[PDB]
Length: 123
Length: 243
Image 1 (cartoon, chains in turn purple, green):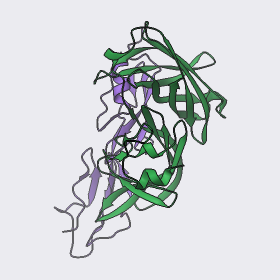
Image 2 (cartoon, chains in turn brown, blue; image 1 turned 90 degrees about the horizontal axis):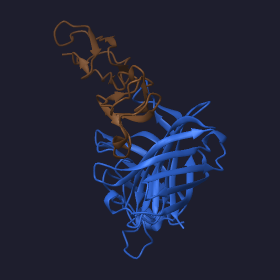
Image 3 (cartoon, rainbow over the protein chains, first blue to last red; image 1 turned 120 degrees about the vertical axis):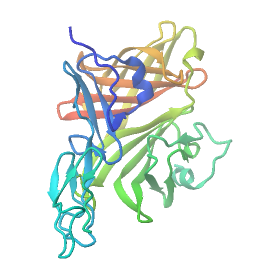
Image 4 (tube, each protein chain N blue to C red; image 1 turned 90 degrees about the vertical axis):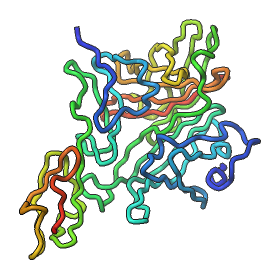
């Protein structure tokens, strides 16, 4: 038989209408529910909300909420990527103005689950 | 209509119920919701109350919405469109018809995107432990989706069996005129009477529905439904009352 899905504990998010949905879990394969992502996080579709589906392999998507890193303004650096959105795992090069550089001889910043690593700032 | 009064006038005890509606799921703690109608304007406020008493019962009240966030002492628009309020005597629900949102790829850009989502579903929750011991009750009301408030909702609850079932009719989109399958009444975390079951179209499962029982004598039902159609998932606002 197919294993029913228990209440989904969505990392950096959760289900809408939690109080009404929670007493009816575990749920059968094929069931789906609208879910949200917390601040600074988004769905694989690029929105703050979508639907999580109970499949034979469990909840789909497996990673419902991914970190979104917005490239900040560089006081003493080149601002072509200012305001540009980057999803978790994606990297971008930091171009600083002459006489300025990253925290420790670095040139690339990566959007991790917690945010930018390292912090994009020219001196 | 009472749209301007709902935004400007303070809370009055003599007003027709539901008098007040706490905006919790409609406005997040970090954000602000700016509502405008009939020349009036008001900003909320997670936990702030909407003066529903000034609005008309058994109808959809429409407002222009702006979802704002304070960045450098100024309010910046994240999402805009139409804010819908369906008022009943012991229950009320909010809906968001998104027209514009902040570009998913850029923080400083706004794009035209249409989305329909149910915000709050609140009122005087019926306790699961205070429900009638027996008898059958028929609830008649409205089913409302994107650009359509003409849907008809019929729901029946058997208090002896602690079960409920219903039907949606007259919505412009035929696929949304679904059957609300037989489902058990269960207590929630706060021991409020709730109902959740399957949504069926032509005897095939298309999604789920959830309802909350409202009023001291279980007079009303309010909630939502999420239905799969040929062109994607569509949400429906649900609200019905006893005759």
